[PDB]
Image (tube, rainbow, N blue to C red; front, top):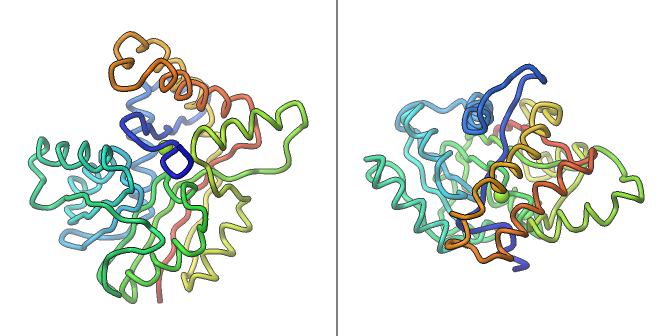
Length: 257
Ligand SMILES: [Mg+2]
């Protein structure tokens, strides 16, 4: 779906495991990665946070319920916006958390209008990621903070895996995929001051095969929301990722001075 590839009701984010002994459920691992990104966003109650690439809205709701922040989440997917808003209503947080349309490259907010920005597994969807980071720096007030989770490429791919990589990128809407150095360089070029940088590939990659397995076991019930091809591409996305070891994962924190 080019710009909409990887977005929709099936936009599922990965999880965090601590070794091969973990034995945490997929939902527990998913909450743990969210909690890892929350730890990198030093906001407090009544701060205002912009959630770029809100997915289905669950991380924004966990952030709001944990830290007491107000959240506006954005996406180009009307399905994601609708799902997220209904989730906020169900969670009794509609007065603190809302979702609306926006292209992250042209954020419809004034300058210095947010205390924080949250971008979990979202910035890879932007064809011009630097422009998105510049818009983030614009809407952050001075002293505003940013917390990013995203895929990174740890190095070149062995030729036998090269087309699995392109499948993963095409199917998942990974329009921007770089190494850590380029990511850190873009953050600085956008006017943001990097405050932390964590390579958590070893903790996150195990969640890829397990997420594929969970979707396989749910075939019967997913097919209403997504066609047989939608569910196939969904399962393929995560199984592709599990086969290419160079598809890593990193958390970044930054501050606008
Ligand atoms: Mg996604």
